[PDB]
Image 1 (cartoon, rainbow, N blue to C red):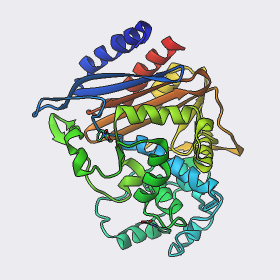
Image 2 (cartoon, protein in one colour):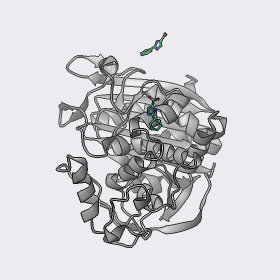
Image 3 (tube, rainbow, N blue to C red):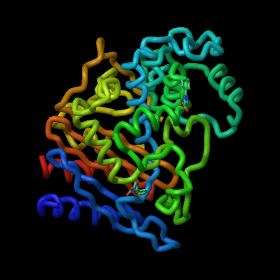
Image 4 (cartoon, helix red, strand yellow):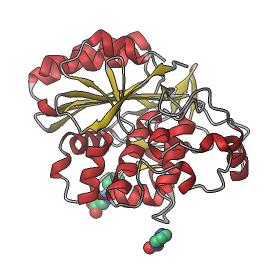
Length: 355
Ligand SMILES: O=C(O)c1c[nH]c(-c2ccccc2)n1
Ligand SMILES: O=C(O)c1c[nH]c(-c2ccccc2)n1
């Protein structure tokens, strides 16, 4: 890399790893559109396997950005609309609280208080129907944001119904393949297991458990190289050859709702650039129910935004942030779930210096 980039990344990440006791980490900086890669520590402590550019990390909720984009792609294909009622794609959702809950509400955590987690006890798919049928909104649709896997997870399952593809097939063929994300997986194939890092919770090696709507909400694993490429695509959607994908990206970065300084996209979340670092840093701390202001009609993707997403599993912590107008981005993948504000802080420190 250029020395400027080498120096800011290292002087920022090294202390962070030390402070947080992160066993392994990979970082990519997109600078004037090109990727620069850094790796530290261990993919697998027991087997002494280092983190490389081919190491797979659990993205956790950064998976939601893929889901938003696949969702946006289905829109641009004319297969679904965000203004459609949920019942249009799940007619079995006959319970009366569902009247007026749209795909928009599902994708943006504004349905009326769908819970953060689908319960563990929901194994079968009729258990799932029961869960949504029996769910009681705390609020009218489109009035409060409460971040929820059961909300965007559902949007992801429904968005791919008209295609007739499974979520995974749809994701692989419509998002992963066109973008050349050849080491990105909903389900890690046995061929790639050698590269699958372990996560670490309280010093114990852990992989993400199977659960309802996992793939749609928190189930993607990826390498720093593919993740960099994800940032490049989202930075420059209009260089993407596939028409509906290109628009899908643009749709995921539209501003549908505003809470405080932040705007809710599809998966992605957005602030006006330049940004107050304390507004993103403290903003990122991990139930926070917030009133939302509808942006009528949604603002198309603003190039002068800080576009970002945090993501966690029991054993992993990820962060992606990019600034379209600066052609600037960062991916940070760690095999420990460490505080969000530390991530955002490291990321702002790096990006601010290169801007
Ligand atoms: O193997 C295939 O080509 C395949 C997999 N799924 C489909 C498909 C499913 C629903 C509607 C259209 C095609 N084709
Ligand atoms: O033909 C090749 O060189 C080729 C295609 N894919 C790979 C590859 C497979 C797994 C991990 C990394 C590269 N090599």
